[PDB]
Image: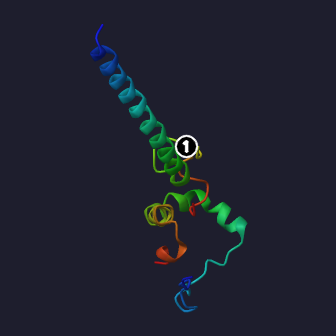
Amino acid sequence: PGIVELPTLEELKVEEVKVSSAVLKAAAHHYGAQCDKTNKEFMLCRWEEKDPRRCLK
Amino acid sequence: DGPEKNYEKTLAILQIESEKAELRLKEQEVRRLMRARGDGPWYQFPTPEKEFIDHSPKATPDN
């Protein structure tokens, strides 16, 4: 009955992390201990909000 | 005994039999309403026990 609200294609534009999985996995342990606070807030947003549109920042 | 006893006993019986008759008619009216509307203590039919819903955080966010 409602109209699903979707962000416009320019709301979804960011600079991508275009590196292969091995590159991520090699740097995975240090990255987890360096980008932790930023990372830990997005996951909190995602489980608290249960909505991908609410955490696009 | 005198007529009093038989008379006033018959009055006592008629009252008992009359009160019962109205209760029996009132129970049919009650049972008709509880069953059709489910808003009374009777004819409550089971719905799944909510205590067994898993409220923990899940492997995925959207839940």
**Hey, which quadrant is residue A8 in on the image?**
bottom right
Q: Which residue is drawn at 47% across and 61% down?
A: A40
Q: Residue at x 42, y 39 (%)?
A: B22
Q: Residue at x 55, y 86 (%)?
A: A3
User: Can you give x and y, in whole percent of width and height, for residue B25 in the image?
Assistant: 48, 42
Q: Which residue is drawn at 61% across and 54% down?
A: B59
User: Can you give x and y, in whole percent of width and height, for residue B11 in the image?
Assistant: 33, 25
Q: In which quarter of the image is the N terminus of chain B?
A: top left
Side (left or right) of B52 relative to B21: right
The residue singled out by tag 1 in the image is B43
Q: At label 1, which amino acid type do we have?
A: Tyr
Q: What element carries label 1?
A: loop
Q: How crowded is mark 1: few (under 14 residues within 10 Å), some or many (20 or more)?
A: few
Q: Can see residue A31? A: yes
User: Can you give x and y, in whole percent of width and height, for residue B14 in the image?
Assistant: 38, 28
- What chain letter is assigned to the residue under label 1? B
Find the residue positioned furthest to the top. B1
Please name whichever residue, A56 or A32, is drawn nearer the observer in this view of the structure: A56
Question: Could you tell me how many numbered marks the image carries?
Answer: 1
Q: In which quarter of the image is the C terminus of chain B?
A: bottom right
